[PDB]
Image (cartoon, rainbow over all chains, first blue to last red; front, side, top):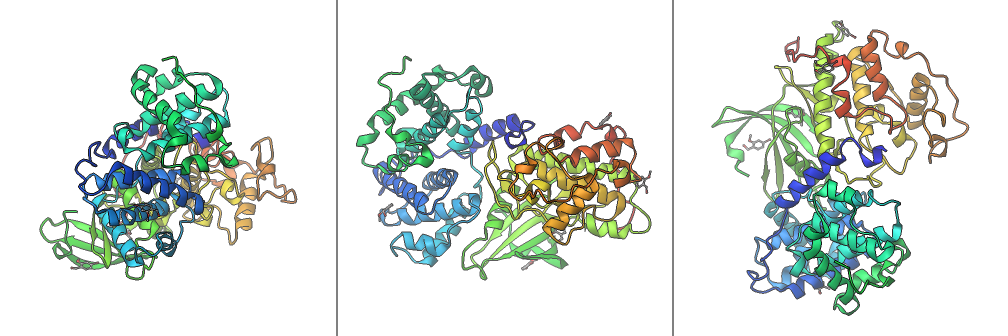
Length: 262
Length: 302
Ligand SMILES: COc1cc(Br)ccc1CO
Ligand SMILES: COc1cc(Br)ccc1CO
Ligand SMILES: COc1cc(Br)ccc1CO
Ligand SMILES: COc1cc(Br)ccc1CO
Ligand SMILES: COc1cc(Br)ccc1CO
C-alpha cells in the first residue's frame, strides 16, 4: 500500500536513475591521489562498518557516507593521516541526514581515539558540505535494493539480507566497484542473492522496471561473484562479522554458488 | 555559491525560527527581493544543524513553481545564510486578513490545486514535508501559493522505513502518527492538505486539539471512531486503546457545511482514515472540484 508509494514508485525510480549519474564519483580518482590507495580506502570503509554497528546506525547511513567520501576524494587530494578525518565527517553528515537519533559530535571524536579534536571534525564537516555543495540526497545501493525486493514472489528475508550484504561488500573495493552505479550493483547483488538462496534469476518484472538484463549485468555479476567467493580471505572482515548476526539472518554463513550458469 | 552579503541591502524582519531570523532583503545589482534565512552555527556546538542539512540538500533538488526557490547558500564559518525567493505573505496571515470577508471560492480552488502540484512533485522526488500548515505556505501578489519551511522534511526510500514520530504540527497531524504506527508515508502530507482545504473554507482549524488524545478524539468525533471495517489494522495499532470512545460518523455535509458536492468528495478522500485509501496528490489533480480552476491574483493587498 501507501508504504510502497504506488503512485510515486516509478517517478521515484526514474529520478534516482538520473541522480545516481549526477552523484557518481570519478572512477579513476585514486591514481590521482598521491598519498592514499584503494587498500587504505578499504580500511576506512571497513572501520565505518564497525562504527555503524557500534552506534546501531542504519545501513543507508553507511552507504551515504561512502558516497560522500568517494565524491570528496574525486576532487580533494588528501594525506593519509587525514583520511579518517574525512571519513568521520562523512559519517557525521550521513548520520545527521538519515538518522532519527544521530550520535553526538563528541561521540564521533571519541571513535577516532582523540586522533582529532572536535574542532577538526566540525571544520571538515563544513569542508565536505562545501565540496559537495550540500548535495547529500544521493541514491544508494539500498534505495535500489528495497524497490527490487518488491519483485520477489514471495518475499524471502534470506534473499533480502544477502543482497544487502553483497552490496555492502562492494563499498570496500573502489576497484572495481567505482565503475558501477548503485542501481547496477543492486541489480547484480539481488540476482546473485536470489540464485544462491532460491536458485531463481533476475526477474522480467525488474527487466521491465530497470531496462537491465543479465547480459547488461554480466560484468558486475562476475565481479561480485568473485568478491563473494573471496570474502572469507579479504583483509577486511567487518561486513561478514556483521552479517553473522540474526538481524541479518546469518547470511554471511551461506555458501556462495560455484558457478552462475551465465 | 555565486553570492555575497555585500550585494544584499536589508529591508526588514519578516519571520523567525529555531534557526534564527528571516529578513526581507534586496539585491543591489539585480533589484531582486529575497528572503534571507540566517542560521547561527556559533550557538551550534554540534556543527551544522541536521534541520538545515536536510532543508538545503532537499530544496536544491526541488525546482517547482509551487515550492519556494532556494536561490543560494552563503556559507561562512560563523554563519549560514539561505537566500530564498521573496513572497509577500503566509496563508495563515491572509485567512486572518479575510476574517470577515471570506476567502473567494476561486482562490480556495487555485490555492488547493497548486498545493497539490507542489506536494505531488515533493512526493515524486522522494521527499516528505511533515509540517504542512497555513503558516508554512507562502503566497504572492500574482496568485501563486508555494510550500515552504522544509526544516522538518525527509528524504524517503521505497518502501518507507520508520522515521521520526515527533512529526507534523498537532492540528495537521494524521491519525497514523497519533496512533504510533511503525510506518507513515505520503498520506500524512495529504491529511495536512485536507485540514488546510477546510481551514481555507472556514478560516478556522478543523481539528484544534490541546493534546494528542484530544486531537485524536476531535478527529474521531468529526469523522467517526475508526473500526476494522473502515481501517483494517487500527485496533492493533500501538497507541490504539480498546477503551477509546466509539463515536458515530456524522454526515460529511456537516463537517464543512458551505462545501459543494465536489469539494466534499475531495475533502473526504484527503481525510480517509486508511492511509492506503487516502487520495494521492497526483490523483487529486484530476478531481472534478478542479474542472473550472484558474489562477486569480489574491483579492487583498498583501
Ligand atoms: C587509525 O586507524 C584507521 C585509519 C583509518 Br583512515 C580508518 C580506520 C582506522 C581504524 O581506527
Ligand atoms: C543584507 O546584507 C546582510 C543581511 C543580513 Br540578514 C546580515 C548581514 C548582511 C550584510 O550586509
Ligand atoms: C522563511 O520565511 C519566509 C520566507 C519568505 Br520567501 C517570505 C516570508 C517568510 C516569513 O518568515
Ligand atoms: C461561492 O463562493 C464561495 C464558496 C466557498 Br465554499 C467559500 C467562499 C466563497 C466566496 O467567499
Ligand atoms: C478541465 O480541467 C479539469 C477538469 C476536471 Br472534470 C477535473 C480536473 C481538471 C483540472 O483542471
